[PDB]
Amino acid sequence: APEIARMPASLRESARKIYDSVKYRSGNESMAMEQMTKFLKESTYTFTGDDVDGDTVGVIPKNMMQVNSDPKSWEQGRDILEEARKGIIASNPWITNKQLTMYSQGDSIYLMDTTGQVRVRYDK
Amino acid sequence: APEIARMPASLRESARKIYDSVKYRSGNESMAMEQMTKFLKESTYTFTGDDVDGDTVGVIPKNMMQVNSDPKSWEQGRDILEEARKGIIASNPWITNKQLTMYSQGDSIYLMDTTGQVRVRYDKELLSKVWSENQKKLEEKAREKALADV
Amino acid sequence: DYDGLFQKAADANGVSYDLLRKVAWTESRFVPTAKSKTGPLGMMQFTKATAKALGLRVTDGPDDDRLNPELAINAAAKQLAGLVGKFDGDELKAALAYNQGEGRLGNPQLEAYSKGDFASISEEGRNYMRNLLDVAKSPMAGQLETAELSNSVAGMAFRAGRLDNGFDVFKDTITPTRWNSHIWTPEELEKIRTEVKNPAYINVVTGGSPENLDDLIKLANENFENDSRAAEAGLGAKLSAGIIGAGVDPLSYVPMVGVTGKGFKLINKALVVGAESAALNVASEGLRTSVAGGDADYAGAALGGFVFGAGMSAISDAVAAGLKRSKPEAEFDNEFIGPMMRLEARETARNANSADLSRMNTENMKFEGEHNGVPYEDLPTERGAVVLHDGSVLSASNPINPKTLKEFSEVDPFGATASDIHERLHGTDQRTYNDLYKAMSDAMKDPEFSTGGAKMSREETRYTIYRRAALAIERPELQKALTPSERIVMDIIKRHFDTKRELMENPAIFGNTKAVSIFPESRHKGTYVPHVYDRHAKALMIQRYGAEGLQEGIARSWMNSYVSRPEVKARVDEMLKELHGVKEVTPEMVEKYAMDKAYGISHSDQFTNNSFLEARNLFDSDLSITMPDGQQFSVNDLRDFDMFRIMPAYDRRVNGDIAIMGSTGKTTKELKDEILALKAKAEGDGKKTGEVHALMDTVKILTGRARRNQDTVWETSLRAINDLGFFAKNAYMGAQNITEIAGMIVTGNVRALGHGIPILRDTLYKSKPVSAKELKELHASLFGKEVDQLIRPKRADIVQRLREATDSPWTKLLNGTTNYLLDAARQGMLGDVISATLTGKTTRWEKEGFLRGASVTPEQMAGIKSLIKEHMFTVKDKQAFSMDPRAMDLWRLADKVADEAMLRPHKVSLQDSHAFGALGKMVMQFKSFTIKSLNSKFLRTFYDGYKNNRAIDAALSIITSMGLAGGFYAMAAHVKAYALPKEKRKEYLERALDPTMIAHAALSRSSQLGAPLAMVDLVGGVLGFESSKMARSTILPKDTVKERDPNKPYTLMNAAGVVNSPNKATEQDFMTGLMNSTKELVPNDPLTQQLVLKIYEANGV
Amino acid sequence: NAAAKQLAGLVGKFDGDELKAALAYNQGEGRLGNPQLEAYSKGDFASISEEGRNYMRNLLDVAKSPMAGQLET
Amino acid sequence: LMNAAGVVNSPNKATEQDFMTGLMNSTKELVPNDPLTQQLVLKIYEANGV
Amino acid sequence: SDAMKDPEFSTGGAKMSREETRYTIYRRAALAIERPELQKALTPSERIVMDIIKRHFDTKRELMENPAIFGNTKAVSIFPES
C-alpha cells in the first residue's frame, strides 16, 4: 500500500511502536495493522501522479509541508508543491516517466529525479 | 536518548538497580525504560549547546552542581557552569560548541575542548565556596542600596 | 635534558607523563649532573635511593658517582609509578611521598595527607605538593586549594575553574582494557581457534568481562548466535528497501556493531520499472565472480557505501542550514544526492534484473572525449561529469570518468610468438595473484594477528605470514605446524613458483623446439623460492665485522648445510665434478666455490640485460653459524620475503626471459647481441633504423624493464568496464557501483579533511598564487619522501625490531593510524634535518638529549653525509648515496625522533606550529584531528559500550591514508606550479587543486600499507606493441630485421595449464580483480564506514 | 540488433506496454516527442498528432498495453 | 620437537618460559596438584601436634 | 606425568608402583622404538613419550654422525657405526 510501503521516513520508528502496542492489546495482527495504516494515513499525504495508472511519486509527511500555524496550512502547501511538480515536469522534461520522485529527509521535502538533473528543495 | 547514553557514572551505578526492580512488576521493558528515564531526568541536567542542532555536550549530575546545601542551589550553580562553558568557547576562538565536552568523575565537574588543550576543572568545594562569598557581598550591595531608600 | 627521554621513560611502567617532567624541573631545573645540600647528586636527586631503587626495577645500577643519564631516569620513573600504584590513582600523594621521603619523618605526612591537605604537612611539603596542581587527579588536588574583583556570574566561573593543564587521551578516552592489549599466549590461540566460530567478536566486551578467556568464548559465541538471528533481519530489511528514496539519514543511528552484510540486496520497491525476471544471456546473471564471498564482499561494500553516502548527503544538508544563518543562499549544490540516488537506482536495476532508470539520455554529441576508445560527453550540471553512450552517468571525482582521467594524466605532479607468451603469462599470473590475495585476506584475519591486542601490525602481519609460507616450503618439517586457513597460501605460493620452475626448465612448451632450460641449476630439485638478499640487512651486518665478516659468514653458513645433509652433499659434488675436478672432490674445492659465490652477495649489491635468478646458489641456507661476537648468524636473515617487492618483481623477469627464450633462445647473450649488431651495422644514416630502435623497445617491454609505466590501474578499468557493458549487463552495473562508492568515499574525505585540518585548509588546498617562503619548505618536505623511499629498509621485521631494540600517539592501540603517521612524520623530520644542515645552519637536532642511537660522532657524521650530497634541493639520489654504511644512521635518527617527539606525547599541543616543519605540522595536525575525532560524542560512547579498538582503528586508518594522500599531492602541486611559467599561469595552478582531482589523486597513489599483494598486480592488460607492428610491416621488405620481427609481436595451475589458458582475460577475471583491488580503499565490515561517517560529520564539511 | 535493443529498452524503460514504446520510437524520445510520451500516459488523447496516433494505431496487434484496448475507442 | 637443524638455531642461554616451566615442573614432586591430599596432610599434622 | 596417570597404573588397585610404573612405561617406549611392530599397540596418551624419546635420541644421532654443523668443518662422525 503506498502508505505502508515507502514510509514517510520520520514515522517508521513510531509507526512501529503503534504496531506493537495494538498487537499486545488485541492480538490480531491484522487489527494491529489497521491501527497502523490508519495512523500512517492520517500523518502523510501520498502525492500521486497525473498519469492514469496512477503510480505514486512520494509520501511526504503532512507535518513538514505545513505553511502557517493551522493545519489547513498543510492543506495549502499541498497546492504549492503540486503546482511546482508540474513546474518540474513542465520545465525541460528531458525525461520524466516515473523517474521523478520526491521525499522528505529528516526535515526537507526534497524533490529529485533519479539522476542529478533536477533536485529541488522545499523547506518548511 | 542523551541522558541514558552518556549516563553519568554514579548514576549508572544506581541506574542498574531501578531498571531491574521495575521490570519484575507489571508488563515491562517499556514501563521499565519509562521509569528509568524519568528517574535519570529527575537526577541529572543535560547541558545543551548554544548551537541550533542542538547536540548535548554533557550530563553532569544534579546532585553535584549544588552550591551550598539545598537544591535551589543546584539550580543557582548551573548558572556558574554555563557562564564558565561560554567564556571558554568565545575566549579561545575556534572551539565551536560541537567540540566541547563536559565530563564528570567520582566527584568533579571537569570541562574539555576536544583537543586536549583547554580543560577547566570545577569542584564541589571551590564552586560552592566561591559562590558563597560572591552571593555574600553581592547581597551586601543589595542591602546597602535597599536600606538607602530608608 | 631532554623531554624526549621522559616521553620514552613515562610510557613505560606508568605514568602521568607530565609528572616526570615536573619532578625533573623542580628537583634539578634541567641540569644533567647535580649536587645538593642534603646529599643527593642527580637529576632526580637521589643518593640514598641509589642501590635499592636501581635494583628494584627494569634496569639495575652500579655506583654512587655514576648516576646514569638514562638508567637513573627510568629507575626514578619506576619508583614514581610505584608510588602512584602503591597508594591510589592520586598522583599528588605520590609526589609528596617522593619529596618528603617514604617512611622517615615523611611517613606521618603521607598518612596525614589521607585526612585532607592539612597542616601536619610542612614548608617544603605543602608548597611542592601545590606546585603539582596540574595533572592529576587526586581528590586532594581539588582539596588542596582550598575579571578579578567582580561578582556577576563571570566572576564565579573565573575563580572556580582553575585550568588543569594535563590530558592523556589514553586515560580519559580509550583506556586500555584487559582483554584488548593482551598478546595471546601461544596456548590460548589453540583454544580460540577451536571454540570460537568467528574471531571478530573476541574484541567486543559488554560487561565485564573477566576472567577469563573461558568466559570470552562463551560471550563471543552467544553474541554470534544473537547476531545471525536478528541483527541480520533487522538491518537488512530496514535498509534494503528504500535507502535514499525512503529515505533516512542515518546520522543518529545505533553504532551498528553486529551487521555484516548480510541479507542486504537493495531492491528499492519503486524505481523498478520493467522487471523482466529472467535473463538477457548466459552472461549477466549476477556479479560474475570467481571467488567465494563474491556476493558478500560486494554486499558489505554496499551497506558500507550506502550508509556512508546517505550520511554524507544528510550532513551536507545540515551544514547547508549551518551556513543559511549567515546568508540565505549562495548556490549550495552540495550535494552527493545525485551520485547516491544514481547509485541506488543502479543497485535496484542490478538486483531486479532490469529498469536502468539511472541512465541519462541521450544527446549529444559524443565529443570530445576520448582517453581510451570510450567517447564521453560533459553535462552542464553538477561539476563534471561525463555521460556514457548508454549513458550510465559517472559522477565526477570517480576513478573511471575519462574526463577526470585525462585531466589527471594532464597537468599534475607454426607456433608463435614471444608477445603471445607474455600475454598468456600476464593473464595467468594475475589470476594466481588474485587467488593468493583471497587466501592472504582470509589468513591475516585469524585470531593470532587480530582478535587479541595488537602485536605486529600490519605491514608485519603479512610479512610474518609470507615468512612462514616460505620457510615451510623450503624445509618441509617446519611445514606440518601451520594454521590451516593459512596453509592455503603456502600451497598457492608453492604451486605458482613450481609452475614457473616447470616452465623454465623446458620453455620449449611453445612454438619453438629449441631454447633449452633457461633455469640456473636443474637437478637441484626443490620449489625454488627466489633468494633475493636485502640491502639493509646486509648493511647491519657490514656495520660490525664489515667486509670479511659477512663474506665469511655467508660462506660458512652454507658450508654447514654442505655437511649437515647427505643429499646436498651429493648434489654439490655432482656440480663440482662437472666444473673443475675428477671424481674425488677436495673440501678445499667446495670452500673456494662457496667463498667466491658468497662474495657476490658480500661486496656488490647485485641483489635487493641480466637477471637475479642467478643467485640460486646450490647450497641450502637454513643453519646458522656463530660469529666471534656470539650472535648466531644464518642466511635467511639476509634473505627477503613479503611477496610484495619479490613475487611481482620476480614474475616479470621470469616472464621476460621465458618469452625471449620461446622466441629463439637466451635473453642476454643472444638477444642483445643480435639486436645491437643490427644497430652498429645498419646504421647511423639509415632512415629505417629508428624502426630497429622500435624493436629494441619491444624487447625492453617484454623482458619486463617496462619503463616504470603501468601508469594507472584505472585507465585500464575504464576500457574494461566499457567493454564489459556490452556482454554482461549485470556485472556492468556492479562494477559501476563499486567504483562509484570508491570515488564517493574519497571525495568525502577530501572535503572533510580539508575543512578540519589547518595546514590543509588555508594553504595546501588553497587555490593560488603561491606560498611565499614555504617553497623552501615544500622542496624539503618532498625531498623527505624521496629520501625515505630511497633509504628505508625494504622489509617489515627489520624496522620495528630495530626501532624497539633501543628499549593515536601509542602503537599499542589503533596501530593502523600510528603506522601511517610514523611513516609520514619521519619524512618531514628527515627533510628538516637535511635542509637545516644543508647550506646554512639550524642545529636544534644536533644538540639533543634525544641522543639515543646517535652519539656525538654519528650525529656529526649524519651531517657531513647530508652536506656532501645535496644543494639548495633535489640532488642525489645516487647509488653511492644509498650504499653508504653511515647513511642508515640518518634513517634511524629520523625515525627515532619521529617516534619520540612528533608522535609519542599523549596530548596534542603547541609544540611546532611556529617551527619545523612543513610536513611536521601537517602530521601533527593530523594527529590532532585524530584525537579530536576520538573524543567526539559518537565515538567515545561507542568505545565505552563496546571497546573494540580494532573498529576505530580501521576507521581512523582510512581517514589518515586518504589525508596523507591528498597532502602529498597538494604539496607537490604548488612546487610544479612554481615551475610553471612564473608569468602567472596559475589558472593552471587552479586546474589541478579541486575536489574533483584531489579525490582521484588520493586513489591512484598513496600506499596503502599493509596490503597483501598490490593494486597494480591485480589489474593490467599491457596492450601494445603498436610500434612493434610498425617495425614488422615497414621492415617487411627490409633485409633481415624482419627475420627477427615475426618472433616477438603478432600483427591451481600446473605447467600444462598455463599454456592452454586464453591469452586475453575472462569477464570473471577482471571482475574478481576489481572486487579485490578495491577492498584496500572501500572496506567490508560495514560499521567502520558509519564510524568514518560520524567522524566526518563531527568535524565538518 | 541495435534497433531491437533500443526497442527492448523502450519496452523496458516504461512498462509492459509496447505501444508506448512504438510511439516513443516514432516520435522521438525527448524532443517534441517527450510531451507526447507523457501525454499518452493520460489516455490515447489528442495531445498526440497526425503520424503519432495513426502509427500507434497501426500496431494494434501484439501487444498488450491498456491503451491498446483504449486507443479504440 | 627438535630436529638436528633446530638445536643449532636455538639460543644458548634460556627463555623466561624455559625456566618458568622448569620450576613449575620440578616442584610437582614436592608440592602436589590434587588439592585434597593437601588438606589430608593438614588434618594428619593437626591430629598429631606441633 | 600425563601417562603414568592412565587407568592401568592408577585407577585400579595398586600393581607395580611407583618406581616401576615409570620403568614399565620407559620399557614400552624403548621396546617400541627399537622394533616397530610392538609399537602399533601402545596407549595414545603414552605414545607421546615414545615420540619424544625417539626424536631426542634421533637428534643426538643426526648431530653425532656429522658434528661439523658448527664452526669447524673437520671433525668427522664421532658415532660408532653409521
Image: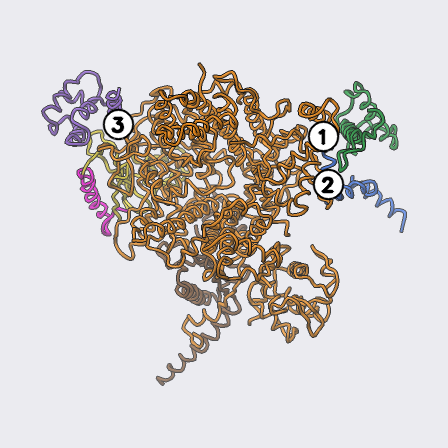
Chain colours: A yellow, B brown, C orange, D purple, E blue, F green
On the image, the x and y values in percent for residue D2 come to 25, 22
Element on which disc 2 rests: strand
Taking the spot 14% from the left edge, 31% from the top edge, the residue there is D32
Question: Observer-nearest residue: A48 or C367?
Answer: C367
**Residue plotted at (36% across, 20% down):** C1036
**Circle 3 sits on which residue?**
D13
Residue bounds of the magenta highlight: A64-91
Q: Which residue is mark 2?
A: C626
Can you identify the residue that label 1 sits on?
A: C589
Residue type marked 2: Thr
**In front: C1042, or A92?**
C1042
Q: CA distance from mark 1 to mark 3?
A: 82 Å
- Circle 1 residues within 10 Å: few <14, some 14–19, many ≥20: some
Residue B5 showing in the rendered view: no
Label 1–label 3 contact, CB within 8 A: no
Q: Quadrant of residue A42?
A: top left
Left or right: where D50 falls relative to B71: left
Compared to residue D52, the image places residue E5 above or below, namely below
Quick one: B107 or B57, which is closer to the camera? B57
